[PDB]
Image (cartoon, rainbow, N blue to C red):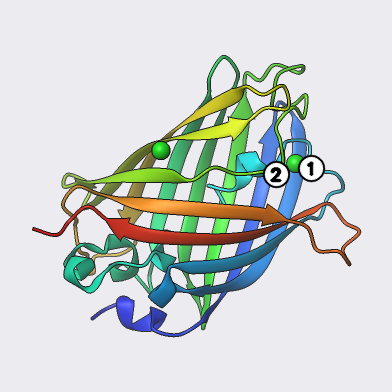
Amino acid sequence: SKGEELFTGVVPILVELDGDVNGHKFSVSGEGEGDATYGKLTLKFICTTGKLPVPWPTLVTTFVQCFSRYPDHMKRHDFFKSAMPEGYVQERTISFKDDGNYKTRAEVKFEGDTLVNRIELKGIDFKEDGNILGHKLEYNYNSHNVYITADKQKNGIKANFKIRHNIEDGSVQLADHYQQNTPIGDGPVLLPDNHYLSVQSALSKDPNEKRDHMVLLQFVTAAGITH
Ligand SMILES: [Cl-]
Ligand SMILES: [Cl-]
């Protein structure tokens, strides 16, 4: 079907983010590939402006849910692939409990044969000595569920979830995520019933890379519709 046929193989990915958090500006480029048949992503991100002024884990969710594995019985409800190749706009607010928030606007679409995620991120109201700008968050990542609902009015979807970032003192920082996705163009989309994505993410470093960077391996599987 439309869009999902573009994901049967391994697809190259490009990620590009312009960020400004509390006035601290940065840019990040990423490259890698996705194999939606297995829900599999492999990505490497490089901060092209120097040192990243926020913890890498805080950007994971912002840096391509069209690569989720939708089981065959759920494929009528895979919005993200259905919008391709024209794509979708993905907007989020990420509210760090007792700290500031990120607002992200992204366009996810094909440019030629490459799946691109172009993002602008703005962060406001952060504590300069908080867990984010104080770099108190551990370089690790928990497994989470992403809860998806249809947005009939906008012909798209919403999602809600709460990321839990381990802090170096053995506590956890909550990062509430509010998400809205809108298809690009007048084409057909598959609006889903309520369901979720089960997401596991592993963060590492490239031993040969001297720039500030993050390697991400992620598995995402849709679930919650069966009966
Ligand atoms: Cl970090
Ligand atoms: Cl969760």
**Percent x, y of residue 197:** 35, 52
Left or right for 227, reference 163:
left
Split into quadrants, the picture shows ligand 2 in the one at top left
**Percent x, y of residue 155:** 21, 53
Q: Residue at x 54, y 67 (%)?
A: 41
Q: Do the CB atoms of the residues marked 2 and 1 lie less than 8 Å apart?
A: yes
Respond yes or no on whether mark 2 lies under 8 Å from ligand 1. Answer: yes
Is residue 40 at all visible to an observer of this figure?
Answer: yes
In the image, 216 versus 155, the foreground residue is 216
Residue bearing mark 2: 56
Q: Relative to residue 115, is residue 207 depicted above or below?
A: above
Mark 2 vs mark 1: give the one in front.
Answer: 2
Provide the secondary structure element on which disc 1 rests: loop
Circle 2: residue type: Trp
Q: Residue at x 74, y 50 (%)?
A: 27
Q: Relative to residue 5, is residue 126 depicted above or below?
A: above
Residue bearing mark 1: 52
Respond yes or no on whether mark 1 lies under 8 Å from ligand 1. Answer: yes
**Percent x, y of residue 74:** 20, 65
Q: Residue at x 43, y 68 (%)?
A: 39
Point out the residue furthest to the front here.
Answer: 170
- Looking at the figure, which quarter contains the N terminus? bottom left
Point out the residue furthest to the left here.
Answer: 227
Is residue 188 at all visible to an observer of this figure?
Answer: no
